[PDB]
Amino acid sequence: MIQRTPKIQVYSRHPAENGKSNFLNCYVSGFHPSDIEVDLLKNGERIEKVEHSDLSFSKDWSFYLLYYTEFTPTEKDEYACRVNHVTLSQPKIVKWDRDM
Amino acid sequence: GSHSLKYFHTSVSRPGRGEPRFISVGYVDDTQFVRFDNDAASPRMVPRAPWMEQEGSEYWDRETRSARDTAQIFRVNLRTLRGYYNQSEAGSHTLQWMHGCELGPDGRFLRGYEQFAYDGKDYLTLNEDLRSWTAVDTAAQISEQKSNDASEAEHQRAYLEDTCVEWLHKYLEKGKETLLHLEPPKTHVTHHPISDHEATLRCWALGFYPAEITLTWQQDGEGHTQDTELVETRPAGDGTFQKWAAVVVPSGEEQRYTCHVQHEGLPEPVTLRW
Amino acid sequence: VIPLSAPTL
Image 1 (cartoon, rainbow over the protein chains, first blue to last red):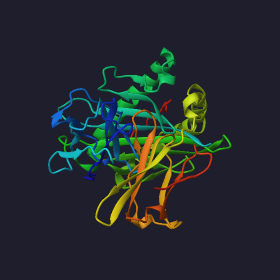
Image 2: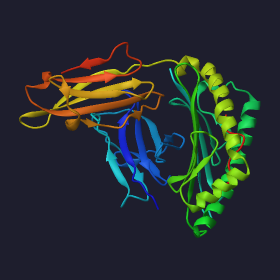
Image 3: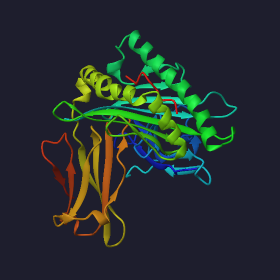
Image 4: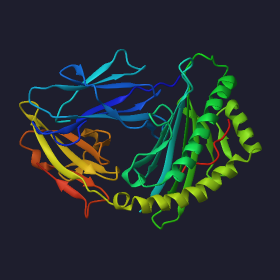
């Protein structure tokens, strides 16, 4: 009956330089149970080829996963992460902000 | 310094939708090096670090046998636990198992541990003597008794004090070029006005390994913990980590705030300012 | 490597 809501961070592997290839990361942590869906979005549309780390957990038993995909940031394109979990009222969208 | 060999195992029932999902992952320190996932394209133990790709088929066979056996016992354990708690065959439940051995800086065994959780809380824990167990409730008391009957702590103690230590040494050799490399943070400050009289200072640490780090802001050389926003240390995706810390300060006063970075990879603690 | 014995609960 213990459920824990995911913490979500959306960020780049390296400081974003427009026009230069990079990796877009969505790190989800602190959640229970383990069943979760994480999608990366470009201009509101789900990116088809996304990879993720193997499910692991912390000393407090909460799960963590990294989802990531290659991307080339630009001034005009918007990126986001969409998380689907039982603790959420509806899928939560977290926008990428290159300063966070 | 100190090193550790640790694994995390998760089994999750999915009634009507197959055998429980079973995932095992192994780490040395902060580096993942193996996994077993019964839903993967190859549902066997497989390398997840470059330095393991050379290991040879006997290693993968023994680890696959062990992992498969663990998945089978966990499947049964999930059924048993349903019976202890009088739960329906219809819900999904989680069994988690974590274990590890830790060497101190002097190269010698410091500690071993092993714990089980059911549905996200402590269930059965191996005591520090590695000879006995603590049960959380009357169900886990039955598990404790069965473990006592089967001398399970003896098997676990031999693993933690011997096998785990032996293989930790082997893995540290196989992966030394990266496992023993300290990668210091690349640090910088960003500055963004937030009102007519205030700005955000954000202190970044990027590209570091291992994950342990301290990032703090000081004001006039004194503690400023209460007014600092800190994010959780997060993976870069290439085996290094990132973190940042931010403070909101009066415009014109930025120079009185200093960011302090401690990491094993730094010759000396670093300080940065705007 | 992982333990050769997985506990039965």
